[PDB]
Image (tube, rainbow, N blue to C red; front, side, top):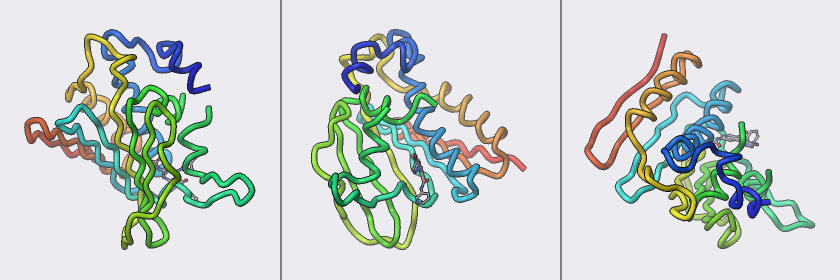
Length: 187
Ligand SMILES: CCNC(=O)Nc1cc(-n2cc(Br)cn2)c(C(=O)Nc2cccnc2)cn1
């Protein structure tokens, strides 16, 4: 399944050779946080372009569920990240690495994937007084060509739009490569 997406990435994510698909990856992750905002449980989304060719999307929602199915021994989070609004599992499949961190029920949970394949089970990594979900991913350089870096104005245009289409949600955009920051929120 993840193999399928890796074989024909352009079908799932858009053109892989001109930056379209690259940016669609970010928007799919953001759409999941927006859905949590539409459900009334997320007030702020922070999108960060890091200086190591990754993007992170952090929300202050309920957190992705962290329970385990007792007979399968697989977490809900893993199911969400690995099984086929094209969906975050596609993003995962087309990422050399993806990091999920969930803050929920007083605990921090984390899992790492490479090309969609989990590296270890979802694990507890601390305690927290906050809630929400963070996805950070490093796009596959076997998939994307020509435009392999995130472009601030593409994200800024669309995040601004998302903030006015979902009035009340605060969307912050941050670029670690030059300190640029924007705050999109509409009343
Ligand atoms: C950075 C990307 N952000 C992001 O994915 N945020 C999310 C996603 C959520 N979920 C989407 C699914 Br399918 C399952 N959880 C949920 C969610 O629905 N959590 C939830 C709801 C009800 C009971 N337990 C957990 C919350 N935030």
